[PDB]
Amino acid sequence: TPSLTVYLEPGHAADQEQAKLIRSAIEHTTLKSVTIASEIYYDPDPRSTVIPEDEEIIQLHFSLLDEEAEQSFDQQSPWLLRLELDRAAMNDKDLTMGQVGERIKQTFKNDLFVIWSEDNDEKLIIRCRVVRPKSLDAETEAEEDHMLKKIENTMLENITLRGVENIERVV
Amino acid sequence: PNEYNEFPLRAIPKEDLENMRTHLLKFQSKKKINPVTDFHLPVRLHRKEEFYPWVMEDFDGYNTWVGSYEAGNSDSYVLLSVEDDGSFTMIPADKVYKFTARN
Amino acid sequence: SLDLDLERSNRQVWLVRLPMFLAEKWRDRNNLHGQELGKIRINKDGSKITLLLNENDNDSIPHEYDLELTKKVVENEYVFTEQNPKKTAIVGTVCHECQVMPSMNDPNYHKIVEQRRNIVKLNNK
Amino acid sequence: ESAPITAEDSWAVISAFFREKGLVSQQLDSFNQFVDYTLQDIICEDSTLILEQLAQHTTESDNISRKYEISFGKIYVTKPMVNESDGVTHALYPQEARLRNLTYSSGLFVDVKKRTYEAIDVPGRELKYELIAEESEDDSESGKVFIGRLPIMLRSKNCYLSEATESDLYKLKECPFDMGGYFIINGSEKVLIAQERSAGNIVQVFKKAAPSPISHVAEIRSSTLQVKLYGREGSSARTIKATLPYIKQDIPIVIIFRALGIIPDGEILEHICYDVNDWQMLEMLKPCVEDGFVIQDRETALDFIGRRGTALGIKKEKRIQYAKDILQKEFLPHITQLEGFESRKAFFLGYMINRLLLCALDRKDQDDRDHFGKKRLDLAGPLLAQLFKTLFKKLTKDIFRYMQRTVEEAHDFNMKLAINAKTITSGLKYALATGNWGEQKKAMSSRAGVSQVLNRYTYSSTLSHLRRTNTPIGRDGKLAKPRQLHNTHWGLVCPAETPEGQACGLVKNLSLMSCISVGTDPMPIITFLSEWGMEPLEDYVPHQSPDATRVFVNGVWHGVHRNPARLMETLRTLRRKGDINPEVSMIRDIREKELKIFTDAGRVYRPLFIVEDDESLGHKELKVRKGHIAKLMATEYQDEYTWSSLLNEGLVEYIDAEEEESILIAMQPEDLEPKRIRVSHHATTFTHCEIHPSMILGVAASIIPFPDHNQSPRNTYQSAMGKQAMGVFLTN
Amino acid sequence: MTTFRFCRDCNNMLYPREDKENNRLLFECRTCSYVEEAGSPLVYRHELITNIGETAGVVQDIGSDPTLPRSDRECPKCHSRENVFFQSQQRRKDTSMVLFFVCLSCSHIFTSDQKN
């Protein structure tokens, strides 16, 4: 049972708030921990859906996407990482939806683009749609599920939103 | 409520069973298969003593069934053959075979 | 020896399960000559079925047993016969499934269960 | 006369119990079972020995092929006796064995028959042998071939001491206060201490810590089968793989079902999952279906099997046949061995993987490895059967080798010369004397301490020594859980009395009323069970009846059932009315809809009372009355009406450590009606009662006065020191 | 909640496939020629944490278990005062100590936690 005890600065020692900010800044946070439903769903035509809840989010970004995104509409995978994200876990680590959800994730490899809502919606729904070139081979393009399940697992497991490695808990 | 019907219990003698060896023919399917429509007569049944499994193939070869012997059926079943007089005659059961359709 | 005889296969056939001792006692060859050895009785509601053995048989066997229904509808079971490549002939389609148990009213039940005790005690392992 | 029962009646019943059974009954009963029944079967297993000598084709007269058949018959056992150096024979009695350093033993006689078959070896044709000569001396006393000498335990059925009265014991100069239960080897007294073992034919689900990819394991010992689930919880990748004997790489489960005979994919999940609605079960089985769907061929899997054998380069068809035979020969032998039982094996594999996956879905917990209901005790009987089987196998192998040797020289063999009768005698004597439970050549790696020299320092020390059990785990092994006292030891093990040092907790002593089961045949139980309305496992369809109780007999699934309550009531009626002997255990688990029946040997059971609801009194009460106690007093003073009289009337019942999981017991009888602090327990549906709490103690601690006013380690210390007092160890 | 669908021909589970010229989803059996039209764009589902209310498990014939306790609470439906009560039979580590009551006569399930 290894352990580590951290003493805060003289100014922040007597107040709980800076202590909780530091605690959030130390603990290891990964995507698999913050999704109440990171559900692998079929996303054949991301233009429209049957579920009314995500329909509201649809028109938000469809009127909020750049010209390059309009061109890349066809790159979005025929499957979706549909993220019903838990409000409590997201707010626990002081994790803003947009900046943390997309900046680092798209910066890492330019692999996964997202349609994401502002935190005010009652159901925090993100649509994670991976981005691939259209130059993909016909045999490759046929095996959509085969690439995307693997990349989805490598996505949940190997993306670090915030924190330092190997530290399971901070108290 | 005591009304009952009468079915006499008869049997089949040894002279008929000597040249009539019975075998329980069981087909594996999820659908009611009847040989009147699903089998085009005549049918070819052969073995290609229990080492060779049974093969029942239709005249056109569309309906081919392969049958294997399932052992350890501790229930010694009986066959109740209905005669012209409405009586039931007993036939002892010798072997049971289970059939499955070829892919 | 190839064609199947379906001219008289339309009639439904009962599927009854007999106890081991009773079934073995009914495999006797001497009683196979079309002899009338027993009778069945069906209740008006059909819930209770009673098998009564004819008095022509020896008094060493119980003359009363009861029947219980397993499935009210029985499908995808057929009865066939095979005679002298061998010539096969379907007998019919199965209708109901029933199972035989000994009757309490006939005291001979105890006797055979007594023999069952005789079976239990002798064999050891 | 319909009155309730007071503790005085409890002591009356206990007095009857000890007046009927005795304190050393377990050894005597195991020895009687071994001598009467198992000894015959050990030889009847390998009765026939065959030699097939083909024609050497040297000359025309050498074109005849020969067959030699050897068969065995009955076993006869004489009373112990000794032949001196002069050749005179006289019956041996324990005094002479003790004083003269002899060995208390008897002789064994077996019938032997021989047959010779001769056939004309015509090339290209099958050999047709015909009976020509048959030597069988059953009509003469010369047919009994002497085979060896077997030691005899004192006071057993064969021994002269069995029927001796007090004056008989005095004139032969016995101590009347001696109980038997020990051998005399080389003129010294030896005893066999019970050996503890983990039960077989029981599926057990374990768990692993996760530095490794393993997540869960399901074990069964019949030959061992391991069906492991790999993949962490919550991940996409689920793998289920089985490890068959003599197959190294291993292959998935859907491949097993395809090779086994269930081709359609939809039937696989009907085999595995018994509830249609549950979706997590099928979600975890999806990757197995996905991977196993690629190959609809048995023969690729059989080719997998064939390569990993020691022989290499075998033709494909022979590999197919070999892998086919492996399944019916070595895959789950405890269910069946002969051909054509595939449905049972498929359903049992489905049940095993179902239980593993259930534990994987947190609906249940790991199996407890300490539960005393999953442990058997081996007495003298089973150990002797083991050693006798080994030695008989070696002896018959030697006979075959010598007979082949003498056939090579074309010399007739004398059956009284081919047998080396000294093998059995020397092996048994060496094993009993040294204690190393194995062959003389391989005694180093065998079990030790199985046979110990009886301790006669004080009478209570002899009593404590003849009632001892050893748990064969390394006494320096640092596993704390086997050492500690466990909740299942109530009434079957003495909590106070245990050694100190390296054998703390590992050596156990029984209480005053914890007997052990002998063994009985399961076939009549199965026959009756199928008679009274049990549907066989062949005709079982999950969807037609998804609320069906499963039925087990000694750990092999035989089918299902629909109305189990009346079956349990009838079974217990028959067990209480003597139709079945009360050493058989019959548990029902309502929550999982299961029935379990045990008839094996090695189970510890204790007596208990019976509570039944009396409507005339308007509440529950025991079946025992003051009339039965008065009859017991009359019979005891007359020293009829004995303990078996109580047993066969359904007044007491033998309960092991497994049925106890499904009962309720009122400890004092007065607790069943509607200083210290005794609390009124809220229960009102009582089923049994404690005959007396004092019996939860052994023989050593039954001499401390007021033991409950003492700290427990003090009771342990005195239970240790009670074996070093000086006193009259025997009156002779 | 994705449900397995079996082919009507050989009972094998149906694999998804796409129709580009009509842009519609179908389920096909890889062994035969059967093809069926998908009714929803929901084919697979992968939840992570289970927000399942604790369940009493098997209830059938639970009143004949004599090692199960009793209580005198009154039935909310049949107004009977005899019933069996037990804790949640799902063995999660973090399960609360919330009781479950099964009525003796009407076999009605309820809990001691009457949260509105």
Image: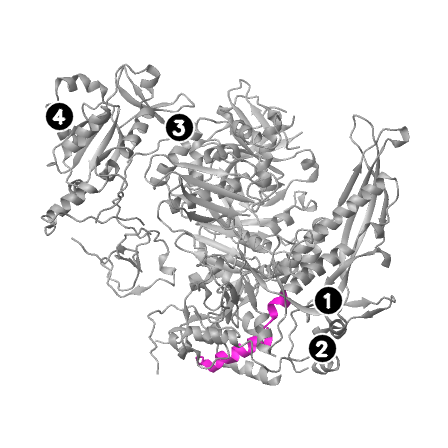
Residue, x 74% and y 67% (percent of image)?
D103
- The residues tagged by marks 4 and 3 sit, at their Cα atoms, a distance apart of 42 Å
Label 1: few (<14), some (14–19) or many (≥20) C-alpha neighbours in 10 Å: some
B86, above or below A11, in the image: above
- The residues tagged by marks 1 and 4 sit, at their Cα atoms, a distance apart of 98 Å
Q: Which is more N-terminal, label 2 or label 1?
A: 2
Q: Chain of mark 4?
A: A
Residue, x 24% and y 24% (percent of image)?
A111
Residue underneath mark 2: D164
Task: Determine contact: label 4, label 3, CB under 8 Å.
Answer: no
Q: Of tags 4 and 3, which is closer to the observer?
A: 4
**Stretch in magenta:** D1-29
Q: Nearer the viewer, residue D717 or D143?
A: D717
Check disc 2 and report its element: helix, strand or loop.
loop
Would residue C84 be seen by someone viewing this image from the given angle? yes
Residue D641 spot, x, y in % from top left: 59, 78
What amino acid does circle 1 point to? Asn
A169, above or below D601, in the image: above
Residue underneath mark 1: D186
Check disc 3 and report its element: helix, strand or loop.
loop
Q: Chain of mark 3?
A: E
The extreme front residue here reads A10
Residue underneath mark 3: E8
What amino acid does circle 2 point to? Ala
Q: Left or right of A83: which side holds C17?
A: right
Q: Which mark is residue D611?
A: none
Residue underneath mark 4: A61
